[PDB]
Length: 147
Length: 62
Ligand SMILES: [Ca+2]
Ligand SMILES: [Ca+2]
Image 1 (cartoon, rainbow over the protein chains, first blue to last red):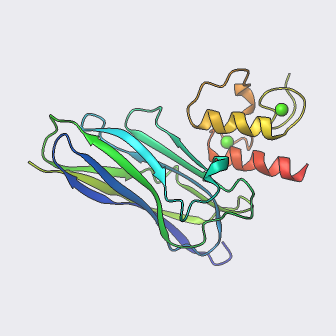
Image 2: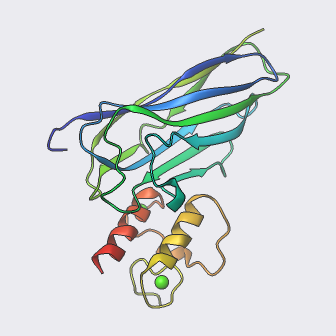
């Protein structure tokens, strides 16, 4: 925040056939200030994909034994990811890398073509260990259904 | 009549038991005994990870 950097949360891309299970990464980049908080929502086409798993990269998201990485899929077509350092000091994100992995199940009767994975830019939150805004930026991904 | 900021279980104190409720609520679990009126800790109109962040801060500052 003193650096006035813009942290980017990006969703990756993946291709798969109808009925396949596909993995797409979520990445954080341009990290400078140690990140203690991340809130982000990812929108997806529910008629085409079913969320199977949303798992963290433990080589970057530490202290997952104390619920530092929370996933919410209670809303159709939306994945809410919340990262928080439970200690407010010991387990920040301080390097660029993969934050989590999204596993989708492609509906067997899904149509071929791209389907965007959209990061809601109005709800994206990134803050330092004392909950002070870090400038954020969203980058969308997608799933390409092959036919 | 719950006038304690972050007291989700309305027991008079702010500790890790309230953190547990916030975490479970943010994951979409049904939290029995939770005071939904106490979730918006920073009074910004939404209940999200920044309320959990504020709650963890309040406990450490106690
Ligand atoms: Ca309490
Ligand atoms: Ca709030």
